[PDB]
Amino acid sequence: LELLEHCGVCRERLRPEREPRLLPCLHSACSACLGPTVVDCPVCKQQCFSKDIVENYFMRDCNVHKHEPLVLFCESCDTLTCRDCQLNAHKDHQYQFLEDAVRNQRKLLASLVKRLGDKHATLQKSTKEVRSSIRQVSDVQKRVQVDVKMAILQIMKELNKRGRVLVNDAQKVTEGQQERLERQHWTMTKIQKHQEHILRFASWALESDNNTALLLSKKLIYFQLHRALKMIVDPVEPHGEMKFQWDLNAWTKSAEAFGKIV
Amino acid sequence: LSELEDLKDAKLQTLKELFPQRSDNDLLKLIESTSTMDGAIAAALLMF
Ligand SMILES: [Zn+2]
Ligand SMILES: [Zn+2]
Ligand SMILES: [Zn+2]
Ligand SMILES: [Zn+2]
C-alpha cells in the first residue's frame, strides 16, 4: 500500500526518471539509492549477481533497435522483442503475439497465487495456535507449581493434627500421674509430721531419766496407744515406670521413602 | 535420490528467508548436522 509504491532509502514515489531497479527478492529501489560486484538488498540478501536485476517498469498513467517499441513475444527466448529482432536475431524462431501469451501467464500466476494464498491462510491460523499454546505452557507451568504446594500443605495440615493429638495424649498422662504423686508427697509429709511429733515427745520424756520415772510411768497408756497409730501407718511408695522414651514412634527410615517419590 | 535432494534444498531456501547474510555453503553443513528437521535447523541457525 503506502510502501509498495515507495522506493528504498529515500522512499520516493516511483519516478520513472529515477531508473528504478527491481531486485530478485522483488524489492524495488532506484539505482541512485544503491550504487555498489554482487548487489545486496536493503532488506533481504545479495540473492543474485547484478546480472539478474531488471529495471522496474512502472510509469503510472526495444533494447537494440532504438525507437522501435516492443509489442511481440519471442516464444523461443521467454521474453519480448520488436519487429526487427525477429528478422535478424530470431529468424524463423517460432514466435507468438502478446495477446495470447499474456492470457496464459496471467492464468498460471493466478494459480500460483491462489494456491500460495491458500497456504498463508494456515499460518494466519497456526500463528494463533502457537500464540495460545505458549500461554498454555506457562499457565500449565504455574498451575502445576501450585498443585504440588497445596498438596504438600494438605499433608502437613493433617500430620500436625495427629502430631498434636499425640502430644495431648502425653499431656493427659502426666497430669494424671502428677495428681497421683501429689497425693503421695502430701500423704508422706503429713504422716511424717505425725511420726515426728510422737518420736519427738517420747524421746524427750525417755531421755530425761534422772528421777523422772514418776512422771513417765503415769502416761504409759497414751505413749503405746499412739505408737499403734504409727505402728500401722499403712502407705508404701509405688514407682511409676517411665515409658515415654518408648512412646516416640521413630520410623525415620519410612519417612524418607515416601518423601523420595513425592 | 533426486527426491532426497529437493527435500534438502527446500529447507535451505528457508534459512535464506530467515537469516540470509550467511553463505549458502555455511547453511548446507548445518542442514546435514541437523538431519533436515524443519525446526531443529532453525535452532542451530540462531546458535551461529
Ligand atoms: Zn529511493
Ligand atoms: Zn529483499
Ligand atoms: Zn528466439
Ligand atoms: Zn529489436
Image (cartoon, coloured by chain):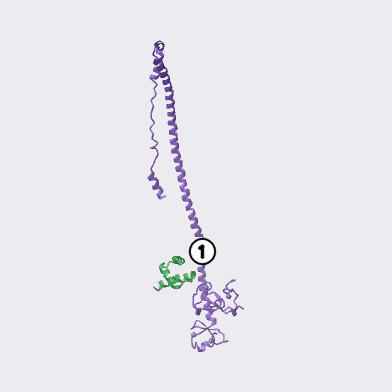
Chain colours: A purple, B green
* Pick the front one: A189 or A112: A189
**Circle 1 sits on which residue?**
A127
Q: Is mark 1 within 8 Å of ligand 2?
A: no
The residue furthest bottom is A88
Q: Position of residue A239 (x, y in %)?
A: 38, 30
* Pick the front one: A26 or A248: A248
Q: Quadrant of the N terminus of chain A?
A: bottom right
The quarter of the image that holds ligand 1 is: bottom right
Total marks drawn? 1
Give the residue displayed 47% in from the left and 46% down from the top.
A154
Residue A166 quadrant? top left
Q: Chain of mark 1?
A: A
- Compared with A74, A190 (above or below) is above
* Pick the front one: A213 or A171: A213
Q: Amino acid at mark 1?
A: Thr
Q: Is residue B33 left or right of residue A122?
A: left
- Compared with A215, A184 (above or below) is below
For mark 1, give the secondary structure.
helix
Q: Position of residue A55 (x, y in %)?
A: 55, 79
Give the residue displayed 53% in from the left and 79% down from the top.
A54
Label 1 neighbour load within 10 Å: few <14, some 14-19, many 20+: few
Give the residue displayed 41% in from the left and 72% down from the top.
B5
Residue A99 quadrant? bottom right
Q: Position of residue A186 (x, y in %)?
A: 44, 26
The residue furthest right is A61
- Compared with A252, A38 (above or below) is below
* Pick the front one: A49 or B35: A49
